[PDB]
Length: 347
Ligand SMILES: CC(=O)N[C@H]1[C@H](OCC(C)C)OC(C(=O)O)=C[C@@H]1O
Image (cartoon, rainbow, N blue to C red; front, side, top):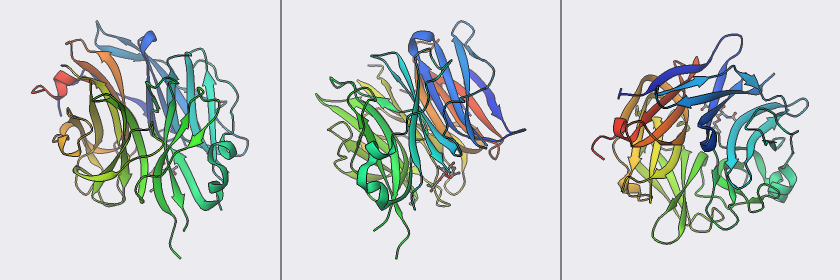
């Protein structure tokens, strides 16, 4: 694999098993919040202080987000987000005991230390369609906050829809313009799209929300939005971003300040038929589908779900990246930290 600043497991199978990582960077505190599902199923958390001089992040003790759950329900798919205009930390998740899935959220005003009680967002965020679905989910992974005047909150999601045939999945985004006070359900993207993530890319003059989703084909599906996620113009398959047919695998995408507005970074297993070899792909001409690069190798061996966070400027001057990913046959969640220079010397 390529050179990295740090490589350590932060969650490890033992008394419990850990899966479905989500990473969040709190810019002003130079630190990260690493969430995971603890499988009696809850969401756990780990806070890490990043120290540049020593090129390392120090992880504190694992904690349970006691408030992120409903009585008699298991919690899944932790989707974190930090509101830069309020200083409020959001943690969206799914609670499960014919649709019976619930959308929830818990907030923290002290950087994750404590959390408000949950808020069941289901009925108002979904409406009548709720009955037309089999189930649904958000993320997993970090969410997105836009540049629009209202600094809208965009939460990536997908739903299993029912038209004889099994429910077909379609990605979409939950949108809030009042800082998570109310929520609207965005429009689906091409059918058969699942777990996805969204990144904002300011190109030309207008904002462009790019969406990268898991599919049932040998390739990834990517869609674009010019209306903050309400509608996703069109979606194209991206041959350069493989999906092992077994059923595919969740992937992560983020935007970051270009070295010369922003570029995209994407992580996902690179093996054609197996969930192995975590690779990093770079898109310097976002969101062009054909601009995606060959993958650079980050981790060898079995790798599954992952989540990326832009961490500012790295020790070498280039963009810094933190990555949380499932590994060794789901025996742990590994935290990886590296720079644009370490991953793409040529760019
Ligand atoms: C909410 C939930 O059950 N998520 C599952 C996810 O469902 C994929 C379906 C929708 C095709 O599958 C996997 C997986 O290892 O591929 C682990 C997640 O925990």
